[PDB]
Every structure is written in structure tokens, then in C-alpha cells.
Amino acid sequence: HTLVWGVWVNGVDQGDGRNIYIRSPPNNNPVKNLTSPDMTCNVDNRVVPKSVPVNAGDTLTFEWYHNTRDDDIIASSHHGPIAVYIAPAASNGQGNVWVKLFEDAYNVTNSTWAVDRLITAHGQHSVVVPHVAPGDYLFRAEIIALHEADSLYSQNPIRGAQFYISCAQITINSSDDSTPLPAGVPFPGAYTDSTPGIQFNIYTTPATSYVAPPPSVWSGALGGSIAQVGDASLE
Ligand SMILES: OC[C@H]1O[C@@H](O[C@H]2[C@H](O)[C@@H](O)[C@H](O[C@H]3[C@H](O)[C@@H](O)[C@H](O)O[C@@H]3CO)O[C@@H]2CO)[C@H](O)[C@@H](O)[C@@H]1O
Ligand SMILES: *[C@@H]1O[C@H](CO)[C@@H](O)[C@H](O)[C@H]1NC(C)=O
Ligand SMILES: [Cl-]
Ligand SMILES: [Cl-]
Ligand SMILES: [Cl-]
Ligand SMILES: [Cl-]
Ligand SMILES: [Cl-]
Ligand SMILES: [Cl-]
Ligand SMILES: [Cl-]
Ligand SMILES: [Cl-]
Ligand SMILES: [Cl-]
Ligand SMILES: [Cl-]
Ligand SMILES: [Cu+2]
Image (tube, rainbow, N blue to C red; front, side, top):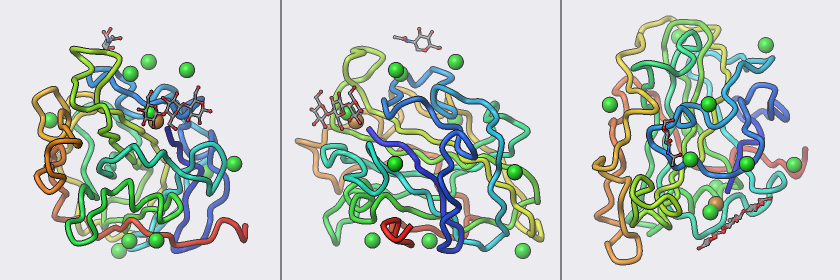
């Protein structure tokens, strides 16, 4: 159970974005139904009044939290990967529009899942804004908690992989459009019951065998990291 509080741009806090520039759901409950429209931008997908201005090459940092800002972030039970996707805002996340900018599953040298590292990073993870067409975009941050993912939701609706999905409204202002945005995948639709990474047993299968759900990260993506960039406590 986790939610996005807001974002930072180039290490600068853009302020509380809940229902402002984040299409926030009413609570931190997971989405589990892979076929539901809730997969796109969670359960209250609507236009919110603000969209955060950034330029290509900026660092955009999502900040997550559990109950209050900079708290335990997400229960440490919730081991799993983290991905960020982008689509143009005009799609409203419909269609084959979602392009992967970032993927982190398990780090063998540190022996930590992306979620493990997100807690250490005080809820913060980032992507570098790509050289896509200027315009309005949705950035869809997705955490998959795998602690009940030995079952499939479709088969047993009290279990299954859990998706903590948050869509940020982001306006790319300065960009040369030198890496125009390629074809995307649909959410819902990209993840199905046979998709690698959706059904997995973290308690018996080595984490080093884990493979995250495709698609693979776009070659045009400029980078990203799970790491604290700013200190909320001074805010
Ligand atoms: O059910 C067994 C699993 O529980 C996991 O904990 C979650 C609880 O199941 C869930 O009810 C609780 O939801 C809270 C939420 O955390 C809180 O922020 C919100 O205000 O109220 C919700 C309840 O209405 O979330 C916790 C996770 O934080 C365990 O992590 C898991 O190991 C366990 O097997
Ligand atoms: C999953 O979502 C689909 C599409 O909205 C819906 O028909 C189905 O009823 C959902 N499953 C459950 C258990 O709610
Ligand atoms: Cl949970
Ligand atoms: Cl609810
Ligand atoms: Cl659901
Ligand atoms: Cl709906
Ligand atoms: Cl605005
Ligand atoms: Cl808060
Ligand atoms: Cl960190
Ligand atoms: Cl540029
Ligand atoms: Cl697909
Ligand atoms: Cl980064
Ligand atoms: Cu939870």
C-alpha cells in the first residue's frame, strides 16, 4: 500500500501534487485485475488541474509514501520491481500508447528488490525526460508487489500480483523531438496471466531468476534510478 505524494524536477520539489498534477486514487489499495481499466491510471483516472513543466534531459523524480510523507513508504513485505512508462496525454492512456522508460527488478550485487531500494530512497525514483515531441504527457509509475503473486487474481481474487499505479501529468516544454515517441503497449492489456513476472513465487524461486514483465525499456530512454534526490524533512 503506497501512493505518490508528488514529484521533483532536477532535485527541486514541485510541491504536493495529490489530485493536482497526480491523478490520485482515494487510497493506497492495490489494483489487481489485469483486464480492468483501473490498470491504466488506477481507480480515479481523470484530468487534474495542473501539469508539471519539464524540459528534455531534466530529472523527474516520483516520491511515494504510505500514510504520511516520508514515512515507511511501502511495507517491506511488498518485494517487487518498478517501472515507469510514458504516453501522450491526448490518448488518456488508451490504446497502444505506453512506452517504457525505466525498469528495475532485482539487483544481484546488493541482493535487493527495487521496492527494497525505494524504501531506502525515501520513496524516490527518477527518470530522465526523453527527447520526445513537446506537449502534454502522462508518466505512469508502477510498483508491482509480489508477496501474493504465487496465485493469479484471475483464478483467486483474494491473491495475485499487486499494482500500485500512479499517473502524473507532465508538460515537456523544451525538447528537440530528436527521439520521437515509438509505438507503445496498452494498459490494461500488456500484462496477462502468462506474462513473465506476473505469477512468481518469491519465497521459493531465487530472485535472480525473476524476469520483469515486458515491454523492454525503449532504446531512446535517457536514464533513471531509484535514489533519494531531495530531503522532504527540510520541506
Ligand atoms: O493481508 C496479509 C498481508 O497484509 C499486508 O499488509 C497490508 C494489509 O493487508 C492492508 O490491510 C493494509 O492496508 C492499510 C494501509 O496500509 C493503510 O495505509 C490504510 O490507511 O489502511 C489500510 C487498511 O484499510 O496495508 C498493509 C500493508 O501496508 C502485509 O504487508 C503482508 O505481509 C500480509 O501478508
Ligand atoms: C476484472 O475487470 C473486468 C474488466 O473491467 C471486469 O469485467 C471483471 O468483472 C473484473 N473481475 C472482477 C473479479 O471484478
Ligand atoms: Cl498489501
Ligand atoms: Cl476503496
Ligand atoms: Cl483490482
Ligand atoms: Cl472505471
Ligand atoms: Cl498547469
Ligand atoms: Cl502527508
Ligand atoms: Cl538513496
Ligand atoms: Cl532537447
Ligand atoms: Cl502488449
Ligand atoms: Cl536518474
Ligand atoms: Cu499493500
